Image 1: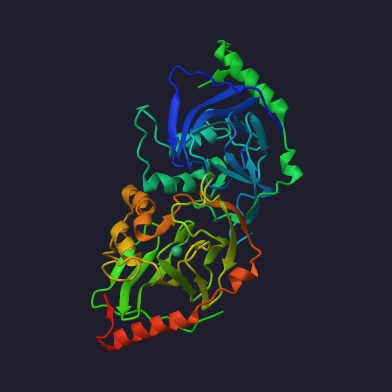
Image 2: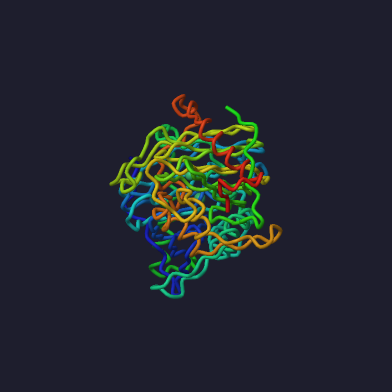
Length: 234
Length: 233
Ligand SMILES: [Cu+2]
Ligand SMILES: [Cu+2]
């Protein structure tokens, strides 16, 4: 099992706290430096929370599970063309494999893979996501490859820490329907993109990693948190 | 395994309900001296259909006039309503998928975990029959509970072209109230689920009960002829 010791959060003066339509509590920020741009969210996942299967085109993603418990789903197949949805009528639905995450496990998911996750437990579980701008991403306002812009556009702001905002039908539908604008094909129901869910995890998925880029993004976050003005987080 | 037709009892004022599982239902309950059941002629929009659940009060038939609908079904049975298919209870379960064909009839006895979805981009028809089983308590329509369930949790459709919006309370109740009506209903798709496989076991493929369906069709047909020895409402 590939683990990672810590992924810190850039501490903004005005944190952006969002309750996603996938029932996830996000503290999210965008960072960039000369050589890199990304979004990062420190998240809490209540029981049953997590996104339906989806595929990214503008970012590579890391999942870090401090307490494990999170069940991730991941394809072996890649879907390199955003215009071809992995649906029954078209190119065809995908085979996914489940990962029973362990404490401080680091999962790397390159662009074009299908993935998702759920908290299948009764605990409210921590997870950190890092979404790094890839080499074909268009330039978004925060130069991050589009993911914070997506969550900010689709998820209500948590203005009251002790009362989570109401999620509406429109917000749930938008979570899927706005996603392509941010280089995401996001399914609206669990079985839309999915053919099978198997528990025997192929070693090729299991082996995927990119610590070098994660370590660079950690240097950026840590620098921002020390007041270094050569990087920006906002 | 196919079935030629399952007719709908024609009520003066059909009961049209949009379920919190995004199903458009034309539903009724019927009973006669020996038998009680609910039936719905449904249209399932893209992505519609219930998340995995298990029945305690009924045996269920699914009939897919145009196929298309994808069903999910366990081999394992869960005979104790107080033991959920979750860590700590019975354990999360293995499901097997069924890609339905035209006029296919799928029989699902009580205690099996099942569900379905319309995975296509067009609305599809399905007919449900839920037959009151050996142990079901007595509900007002004597049907084993299913019509009372849907009528309690889901809104009436006042206009098929302008479907009612489901509320958060309705969706919550579809899960939370289900055990009162003899259903353990999951609130997210993978709650009760370990794996989903496309290799359909023969022990599931062979499930059938044409004899009880034929009895229930006879009740419906009799009701539709005006026979007062049976009731549909
Ligand atoms: Cu993702
Ligand atoms: Cu059922």
